[PDB]
Image (cartoon, rainbow over all chains, first blue to last red):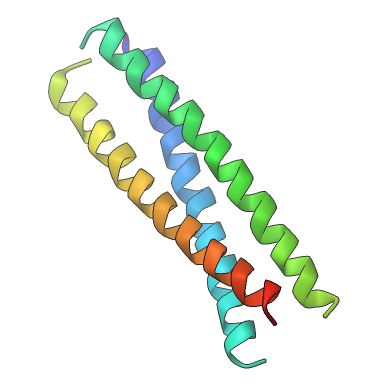
Length: 37
Length: 37
Length: 37
């Protein structure tokens, strides 16, 4: 396994961590809307 | 690091991207339900 | 690509699967709250 292909995956995982953070932010916002509804 | 083990991880990341897409679809649906409630 | 660096990524993916499971649990809980509201 070469460095280039491995970095492709590292870049994707980092991207997904960002996607997960955004999803967590959205779900937590929804949770607050329901708690105060 | 061999190709076989690396592909196991590549397959898992691809699977997780699908899981993330589904989660995003669900959260966006919930967001719309709250906006029109 | 060495074993050490590859394991760093394997550990992170495993962590993210846990993060995804928690997000799925939260979104499913929200979905039920809306269905019974």
